Amino acid sequence: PPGPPG
Amino acid sequence: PPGPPG
Amino acid sequence: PPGPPG
Amino acid sequence: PPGPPG
Amino acid sequence: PPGPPG
Amino acid sequence: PPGPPG
Amino acid sequence: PPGPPG
Amino acid sequence: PPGPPG
Amino acid sequence: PPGPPG
Amino acid sequence: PPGPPG
Amino acid sequence: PPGPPGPPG
Amino acid sequence: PPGPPGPPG
Amino acid sequence: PPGPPGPPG
Amino acid sequence: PPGPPGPPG
Amino acid sequence: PPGPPGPPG
């Protein structure tokens, strides 16, 4: 899955 | 695994 | 079978 | 056997 | 992460 | 997200 | 931050 | 924001 | 700040 | 503001 | 034979 | 494979 | 990635 | 960024 | 900035 937001 | 942070 | 997700 | 992780 | 101050 | 105001 | 005095 | 008045 | 005396 | 009168 | 890679993350 | 980067902040 | 600068003051 | 100067006095 | 001179006396 997509990584965490920055 | 989840990707890297944004 | 397909491996586990990443 | 199951394949490798994605 | 949140960006820098304005 | 946008940083804090200056 | 707030700007300088006038 | 605008600085204080002079 | 207030200006100088007249 | 305007300074004091003279 | 083993199976193929898995889905991305 | 890992997943892609995440959204910006 | 980090987010962009914030608004001015 | 900081804000701009303030009004005169 | 400071304000301007004041009125005369």
Image: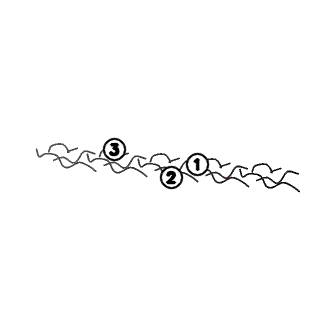
Chain colours: A orange, B red, C cyan, E yellow, H green, J blue, L purple, M brown
Q: Residues within 10 Å of mark 3 (few under 14, many from 20)?
A: some
Q: Secondary structure at mark 3?
A: loop
Q: Residue at left 18%, top 42%?
A: J4
Left or right of H2 in this view: B2: right
Q: Which residue is mark 3?
A: H4
Q: Secondary structure at mark 2?
A: loop
Q: Position of residue C5 (x, y in %)?
A: 75, 49
Q: Which residue is mark 2?
A: M4
Q: Mark 2: which amino acid? A: Pro
Q: Position of residue M7 (x, y in %)?
A: 43, 48
Q: Residue at left 72%, top 54%?
A: L2
Q: Quarter holding the N terminus of chain J?
A: top left
Do the dots labelled 2 and 1 sit on one chain? no
Q: Residue at left 30%, top 44%?
A: H5
Left or right of J1 in this view: H4: right
Q: Which residue is mark 1?
A: E1
Q: Position of residue B2 (x, y in %)?
A: 70, 49
